[PDB]
Length: 328
Ligand SMILES: Nc1ncnc2c1ncn2[C@@H]1O[C@H](COP(=O)(O)O)[C@@H](O)[C@H]1O
Ligand SMILES: [Mg+2]
Ligand SMILES: [Mg+2]
Image (tube, rainbow, N blue to C red):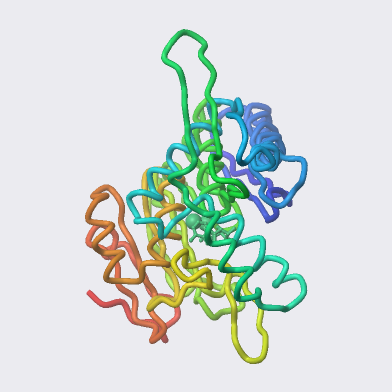
C-alpha cells in the first residue's frame, strides 16, 4: 500500500486528491494526471466568471435559439433545475443577473443599487430554462434560456458535480480509496488505511475560524460532505457584512438562523445543491425539505455554537473544539 496526493490551483480554488492504492504507482500517477486535466477542461465548460467558457456562451444566447450542449452539462442542468423546483427556488441556478451585481460589490466594496437589483430579480426565473433532448439515436441535447437577460451561475453545484466526476474517473482507474477535496467540497471514497481500514475523518470548520483547524470531525465512507456558510465569502461596508449566498426572494445575502449547513450524500452534486438551499431556507424549513431526501444526512452549526445532526450521522460526529456542543 502506498499513499499519494496531488494538489493544484484550478476552478478558482485549491483542489487536492489523496489516494491509497496497491496498484503500480504509474497507474495512480496516470489517474491523477487525468483528474487534474479534467478539472482544467471543466473550468472551461462551467465557469461563470470567465468570458470564454461554454456557460458564458450559453448565457450570451439568452432570449434566442436553443443551444447544443454536451450530455454532461445537460445532465448537470437537469439536476440543478430539479433542486430548484424541490427547494421552491431557494437554490436557483439562474441567479446570475443578481450574483454579478453583488460580485462587483465584492471587488469594489459597494452594495448594489435598489432599482438595479430589483430589475435583476426579474431575470432569474429558472422555470424559463428549457432543456430538450430528442429520443432518437444520437439526438442532440439543447438548452434554451427563454427570458431575455437571464444568466446561469452554477457556483452552488459545480464543485459537487466535479467531485462526482472525479470519483467516477478514479473508479474507472480501479481505485477505491480516495479523499477528493475541491475547495472544501469533499468526497470520501471508500476507506482509508491506518492492513487496518478505517473511515475517513472529515473535518467541518468553525464558521468564524481562521479555517486552519476543524471544529468537528465526522467519520464517513463512500459519502460526500459539502458545507455552505455565511463566512466563506463576503465583504463588509459600513459595519455590515454581505455574504455570497443570495436569498432569491430578497435579492440580498440570505438572513438565516444557521451559520453553516453540511450535507452528507452519496452524490456530491446533490450535497452541494442541498447545502445552498438549506442555508437559504434556514433550519426548520431545511428539515422539512430534507424529509424528501431520506438518503441524505445533515449537520447544522448555529450561531450559539450548538450543533444538530441527523440520525444517520450524529453518532459519527466528534467535537474537537469544546466551545461547540453536539445536541443528541
Ligand atoms: N441561492 C442561490 N442558489 C444558487 N446559487 C447561488 C445562490 N446564491 C449564490 N449562488 C451562487 O452559488 C454560490 C454559492 O454556492 P455554495 O458555496 O455552494 O453555497 C455563490 O457564490 C454564487 O455563485
Ligand atoms: Mg452548494
Ligand atoms: Mg458549494
